[PDB]
Amino acid sequence: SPGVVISDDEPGYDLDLFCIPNHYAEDLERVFIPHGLIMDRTERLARDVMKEMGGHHIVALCVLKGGYKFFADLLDYIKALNRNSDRSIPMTVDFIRLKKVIGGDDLSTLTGKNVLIVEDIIDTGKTMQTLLSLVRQYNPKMVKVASLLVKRTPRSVGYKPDFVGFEIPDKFVVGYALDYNEYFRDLNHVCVISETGKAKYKA
Amino acid sequence: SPGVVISDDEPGYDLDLFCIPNHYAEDLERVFIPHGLIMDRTERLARDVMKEMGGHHIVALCVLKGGYKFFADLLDYIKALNRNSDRSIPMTVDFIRLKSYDIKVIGGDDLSTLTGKNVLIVEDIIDTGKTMQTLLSLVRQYNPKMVKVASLLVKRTPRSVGYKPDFVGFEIPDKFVVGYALDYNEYFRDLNHVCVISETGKAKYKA
Amino acid sequence: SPGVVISDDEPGYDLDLFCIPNHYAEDLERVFIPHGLIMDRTERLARDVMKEMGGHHIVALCVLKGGYKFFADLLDYIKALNRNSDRSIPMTVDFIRLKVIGGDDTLTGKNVLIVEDIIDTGKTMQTLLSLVRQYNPKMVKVASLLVKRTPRSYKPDFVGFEIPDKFVVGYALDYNEYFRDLNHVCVISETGKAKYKA
Amino acid sequence: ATRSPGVVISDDEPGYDLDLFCIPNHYAEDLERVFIPHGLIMDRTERLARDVMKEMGGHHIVALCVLKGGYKFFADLLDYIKALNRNSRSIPMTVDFIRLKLSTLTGKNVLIVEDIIDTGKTMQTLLSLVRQYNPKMVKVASLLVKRTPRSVGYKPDFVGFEIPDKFVVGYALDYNEYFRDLNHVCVISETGKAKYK
Ligand SMILES: O=c1[nH]cnc2c1ncn2CCN(CCO/C=C/P(=O)(O)O)CCP(=O)(O)O
Ligand SMILES: O=c1[nH]cnc2c1ncn2CCN(CCO/C=C/P(=O)(O)O)CCP(=O)(O)O
Ligand SMILES: O=c1[nH]cnc2c1ncn2CCN(CCO/C=C/P(=O)(O)O)CCP(=O)(O)O
Ligand SMILES: O=c1[nH]cnc2c1ncn2CCN(CCO/C=C/P(=O)(O)O)CCP(=O)(O)O
Ligand SMILES: [Mg+2]
Ligand SMILES: [Mg+2]
Ligand SMILES: [Mg+2]
Ligand SMILES: [Mg+2]
Ligand SMILES: [Mg+2]
Ligand SMILES: [Mg+2]
Ligand SMILES: [Mg+2]
Ligand SMILES: [Mg+2]
């Protein structure tokens, strides 16, 4: 699927209807995707991943930093599947940051393996284009990408992930490990940042 | 606060986007309020409840059967607040059911247990408001210190007698919904999301 | 299966290592079964129930008041299996209390799961079992979070934990209506017994 | 003093029969016993989060995750801290990750989050680097601390569980990269040890 489509005229939710940390009370305009909705969608993505990749060992590759929450949660739902079903296949994990690929195991660990790349957001698609090209230099057996969010944008190079949580307008969103200048990662919901927030936290 | 307002024209979500019990697959039309959204809203309600009612022993009254899930979850969020704050208050629980013949209270403790306590009535849905006005009239006779009502859902309807609860999860259109313990002829309680039921479904489970 | 066997000499855990409501700080002696451990065991019980009772339609019967938490959580784990795995319920629910308030009068030809907080003398369970059986169900099974090792003049089909003959409270189990608002199962202290004595 | 000493697990702790829990099929033969149930980890971590906030909540916290084994404890501990921050009076928090085989820290309350302390060498090594970014304060939370005469004597500030000298896996802790995808902390069978060395 293209995922849960959040349309351009999505009002999202007033902050006052949810529990929000006091230190961000002025810096957010609206809740855009409630944490629990992310959980529900992620539960279903875990099933789609297993239906598609469950027949072999998987190396799940977390794209730090923004990917960390989605990754942990997605893997927790896969694990729940694995321990309540007859069949299960093991998973190993690894972590990388992009700048060139930094950190992470020798990517020869991906050689001949089924790789699941887990990302927070695809925008132009350039980052994923680049990572896919890098990973493929190490001859994995299979590579699929899961991204919590995919933006509708004219800048898209035309790359589309295999698993997508939500398809969103081109608004700047933060929360659930997504940041604005390292802030807002410590927020459970995805939210649209306000202009006041953009100015307080700009570098 | 009328709660999270769901508009008349809200399409809900395609079932294929979520994990749905197989046995209800063609009995539902859309997911209307995802479970997780109910959880997030309930977390805020627990905080609102403690702000108003946390000053004295609370008796939380579950209106069975449809109230049971919202009750368990709301109380769990309240317990989480109470074991992570400096000071806390005891909470006791009871369960009642209202039976239609005219409407009367079935079960529960002797209601003298309510005397002098902060009573929180927890309901799945307010529609006409007649059930709650009835329950409130009974409860008040036992002189609680205060009595407040939390309802997961409140329906916008012309048939409303004008009762509004103190705490509201979601304000919804005049559509028939099921899930999260709300039923259609006892079915659909075993579903985590609030959903709208299909034509195939209403027919299948019809009395 | 007798469930998770908690030995007679089990010391439990210091309260100060867990999150506990301050209003019960002096009323508990030890944490006995941490909430999270109840969840882990309950997850496995849900799978055992579905292995044995699914799929025909199940009516899950909640024995109030103490069974309410175990019932809600066990049913949540069963629902998780119903939407993620290769098998299904449907389930309907009812709630009974012994004081027999509620009940719908429904059980005939159905698979009935009685859900109980604790078996001690076994008397509530015998009563629930002669009830239900009068409506000729297709099958009856009993799930009990706790079973005490104590003399008992039916063995439950699904057991969370087999515990010593100690008075425990928490996870909806009460002492004179108190301690239901505690997520862990804990052993009540002497000062707790005196404070909330009726 | 240890700000939050841990659940002491005795040398003769027998753990739990695997058959009493939900275990991934692919590890059914490779594990011997459940040692620390996932849910027990969660309950301890909840109290740990409160202890952290009591000690460090007066100023911006930077939580530093020590990959790979620390990732689960880190995600969960931070989730509990976040819950405290939104149901209260709150303090901003930022995250970073480091792996052993950062101006984000300067002037802030740094919480290093680790899976296990054994000899203490790794933590002493890491501390000696982190201090060079001149934090306001540095604290270490470790899910597990092993009782070993081999301990160089280093003690973290927040401890989940103090365990005997046994090899454990699960909750992101690995044996040669295996067993990370397991929610419980477990002791590894003889067959799993030989199979994955
Ligand atoms: O709405 C947004 N919120 C937060 N970040 C956003 C957003 N849109 C684009 N970005 C940047 C996302 N990424 C930024 C890449 O760098 C991320 C490093 P980290 O913050 O450690 O996860 C680019 C995606 P593409 O190559 O497809 O254009
Ligand atoms: O959309 C709906 N879904 C499920 N049930 C609905 C709905 N609308 C009204 N109801 C009936 C709710 N109640 C029905 C009362 O009976 C209790 C239902 P149960 O929890 O299954 O024992 C009426 C409230 P009021 O007096 O304000 O009109
Ligand atoms: O250690 C204990 N803690 C709390 N309650 C205990 C305990 N032992 C027996 N009981 C009484 C349990 N009751 C439990 C059944 O119903 C629960 C009544 P309530 O939860 O207070 O509305 C009877 C057990 P049985 O009929 O097998 O003898
Ligand atoms: O029981 C165990 N299970 C898993 N690993 C264990 C265990 N005991 C020591 N270790 C090695 C842990 N660490 C190993 C560090 O490197 C491995 C980090 P990762 O990438 O998470 O696998 C040594 C700590 P210290 O300097 O205090 O001796
Ligand atoms: Mg990214
Ligand atoms: Mg960024
Ligand atoms: Mg109702
Ligand atoms: Mg009804
Ligand atoms: Mg009972
Ligand atoms: Mg009792
Ligand atoms: Mg480590
Ligand atoms: Mg290792």
Image (cartoon, coloured by chain):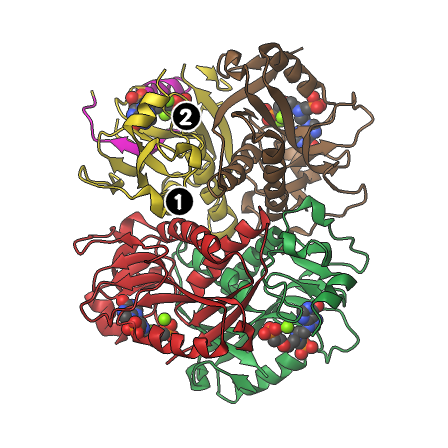
Chain colours: A green, B brown, C yellow, D red
Q: Is mark 1 within 8 Å of ligand 9?
A: no
Where in the figure is residue C53, as x and y percent of width and height? 39, 38
Quarter of the image containing the N terminus of chain D? bottom left
Inter-mark Cα distance, 1 to 2: 22 Å
Residue numbers of the magenta segment: C124-152
Disc 2 secondary structure class: loop
Q: Chain of mark 1?
A: C
Query: Which mark, by number, is residue C178?
Result: 2
Where in the figure is residue A186, as x and y percent of width and height? 58, 60
Whether residue A77 is in magenta: the answer is no
Where in the figure is residue D151, as x and y percent of width and height? 23, 70
Quarter of the image containing the C terminus of chain D? bottom left
Disc 1 secondary structure class: helix
Compared with B81, A125 (above or below) is: below
Seen at 41% across and 40% down, the residue is C20
Q: Is residue A70 left or right of residue C13?
A: right
Q: Is residue A175 left or right of residue D141?
A: right
Compared with D98, A166 (above or below) is: above
Picture quadrant of ligand 2: top right
Which residue matches tag 1? C39
Where in the figure is residue A116, as x and y percent of width and height? 51, 73
From this viewpoint, which residue is outermost toward the bottom? A137
Q: Are marks 1 and 2 on the same chain?
A: yes
Front-most of B30 and B104? B104
- Amino acid type at mark 1: Met
Report whether residue A28 is seen.
Answer: yes
Seen at 32% across and 41% down, the residue is C33
Front-most of C187 and B151? C187
Comes first in the chain, label 1 or label 2: 1
Query: Which mark, by number, is residue B99?
Result: none
Compared with A188, C131 (above or below) is: above
